[PDB]
Length: 126
Ligand SMILES: COc1ccc(-n2nc(C(N)=O)c3c2C(=O)N(c2ccc(N4CCCCC4=O)cc2)CC3)cc1
Image (cartoon, rainbow, N blue to C red):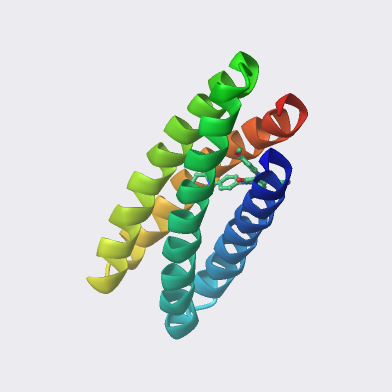
């Protein structure tokens, strides 16, 4: 249902944010093993998140919920903007580029804040 998919997306989204924050703290402390394993976890969560939203969107469209469909389209563009920065961050880390990695973190952090706000809005709109 819209409700069971939404609740799972919320969990998956919260997990992705928490893992990102844990990964950031690890990096500032020079814990690279930890960092890479979180990158694998984050990418995984992002894929599961996209699949859930694609299903909620279809249900939102079918019930005529133009407000959710609009918000979900803003969240998804925002999410995909952040996901492009994440990809470059993974390519950098594997290349030993710490400086590039730190800059990507800050940028991703700021995109993430935009998605969090839109998340709060989607909750009220579905
Ligand atoms: C139908 O669509 C949604 C959308 C959002 C939710 N949802 N619910 C909650 C909650 N109940 O708290 C949360 C989310 C969520 O997705 N959150 C999040 C995930 C990922 C990002 N990122 C990651 C890096 C790239 C940028 C970016 O935006 C930002 C925010 C915040 C937590 C449910 C259903």
